[PDB]
Amino acid sequence: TKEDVKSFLRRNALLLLTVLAVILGVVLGFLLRPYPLSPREVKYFAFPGELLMRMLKMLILPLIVSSLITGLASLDAKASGRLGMRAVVYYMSTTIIAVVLGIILVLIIHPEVLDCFLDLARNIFPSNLVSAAFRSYSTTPVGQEVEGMNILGLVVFSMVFGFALGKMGEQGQLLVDFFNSLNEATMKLVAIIMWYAPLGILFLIAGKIVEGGQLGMYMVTVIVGLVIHGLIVLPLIYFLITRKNPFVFIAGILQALITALGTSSSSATLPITFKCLEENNGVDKRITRFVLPVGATINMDGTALYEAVAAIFIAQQIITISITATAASIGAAGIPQAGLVTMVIVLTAVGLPTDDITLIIAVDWLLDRFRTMVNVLGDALGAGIVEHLSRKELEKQDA
Ligand SMILES: COc1ccc([C@@H]2C(C#N)=C(N)OC3=C2C(=O)C[C@@H](c2cccc4ccccc24)C3)cc1
Ligand SMILES: N[C@@H](CC(=O)O)C(=O)O
Ligand code: NA
Image 1 (spheres, rainbow, N blue to C red):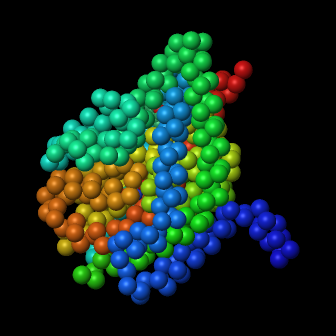
Image 2 (image 1 turned 135 degrees about the vertical axis):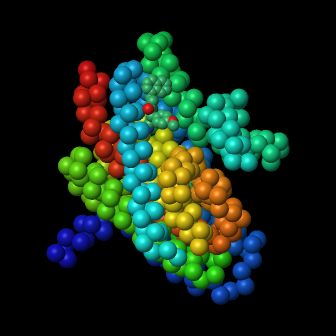
């Protein structure tokens, strides 16, 4: 019994270091909290956590583009459509199951919007690809193009480009071979970036915990709702569909959930979720390159629940809330504080004052660290479900 735990410590070396990083980060952050805090000085303190974020952001661009180009090229017309339909149906249901779970819990325990739709439409079709790799569109930072990255515009273009090569046969093969080499090469860089994660995660959360009262019971509604949907609803869905153990599946992606908690960005933790599914859970690359990049921005289960709870909490009808909370879920990017920005849209539709968001902002960060964990988990189990379901398509692609 105790001799068997030594084989666990030798193997899970990096997984236990990121756990210890959280345990130490919560300690050090609370230890350095009574000291005279400063914006400039907190920025200096949280710098080892800042370098990890830069390393992971560096890899999101060559991952998104290479994954979707090879991923769609490697599949037939009806195959990618069937693969897509299995993913979309899953994405639509899980975000609807989350908002229904969110609305019921907030009802039981009660504690420029056109421009937004236009900007998103403008972002699905970028005017410049070199630009899209570091800028997004936000109508009104110079002009209407905000510094970021159009993750959605790249996902949409790379998809049609991957389809085009998968339609031009052997002429397309060269570029597919080129984009395949690049996908693996960056997946070798995420191996290097993985040994820095325990040091980074420690400082990312220690710095964040160095920063009327009714919000405590609002924070409870969200956190409880995330556990019911995350550790009870989603594992049940996987066990019902795949007929496989979900809590041993969650053990593989556990290294990525901790980094989602540390960074609070599902797009920035994508290179690690890719490594955790392809390696630890042994999910097919032909489907992880398909499910995960789209899952980063479109499937946001934890955000959808947070959009429903926070909208009804500031009321201190439901049909419009459930429709726009699922709408805000899809819209919002896998970036920190994204839910808070899309909350402006979910409050305008119902008729509540948008200035009421100011009450939430203070707590928001701590809920976002868990919101991302459920947003990531929904894609990991999503890929696990789609891989298992698309069994016949994958068997046809082999010889
Ligand atoms: C809100 O935006 C999205 C965009 C895509 C998707 C689906 C997805 C996932 N996950 C991925 N990786 O690829 C495809 C999907 C389709 O359903 C459509 C699918 C598809 C089928 C057949 C031909 C295509 C040609 C070009 C692009 C997609 C094509 C590809 C879902 C939501
Ligand atoms: N932080 C979340 C997005 C949000 O703010 O809801 C994510 O990246 O999954
Ligand atoms: Na989203």
